[PDB]
Image (cartoon, rainbow over all chains, first blue to last red; front, side, top):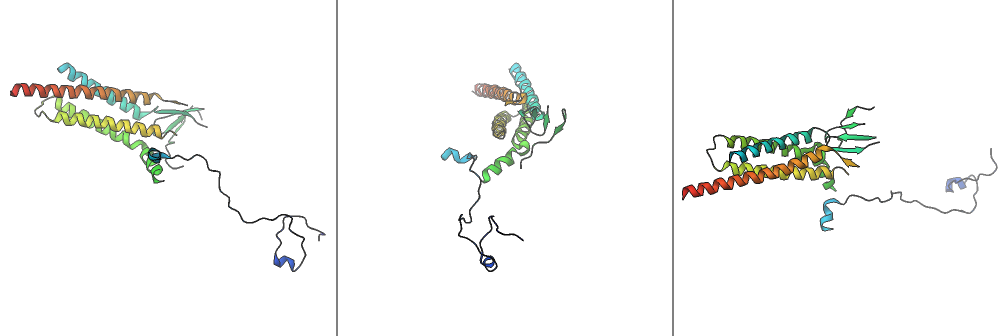
Length: 49
Length: 169
């Protein structure tokens, strides 16, 4: 149905069995998403901080 | 003598009235999402004229405990109950003063009630986080008048103790 696919499609083993792939132009991995640390209320610990 | 006792009585009455006015409404004011007044129970915005209980304590454990103390303003209510009990004890010790030792306990309870009122005022000031309502100033002035009335009451008590020590000798 198509000729060539240019999209972030994950190169897997089960997709290699049906079609081919090029070399990975963009390498990546699994990361950790957390919020930016805003100023939290220190409270009672401030007396002996 | 009796004029100082009547001044102490009307000072306790004015302090209880200003404490009731501080409990009632207009304790704090802050611009919400126009301005809005608050009296530690509900908020009233500037539609216009409606009022709603905006005293929602939920949206370390010390922050949750401070929110629980700030929930429904338990400490100034206990301070007002202790001030009412001290005023009743002063009214009971004013007429038919048979025992010469209940006045010191009533004055100690009155000063401890003022200290608890100051602690609750510190809690309600810490619960705020731009101006402030009239009832905060009224509660502060009632704390000043209550401290002055406690000084006058313990001055009358030490004068009565000196009179008793002079009559016993």
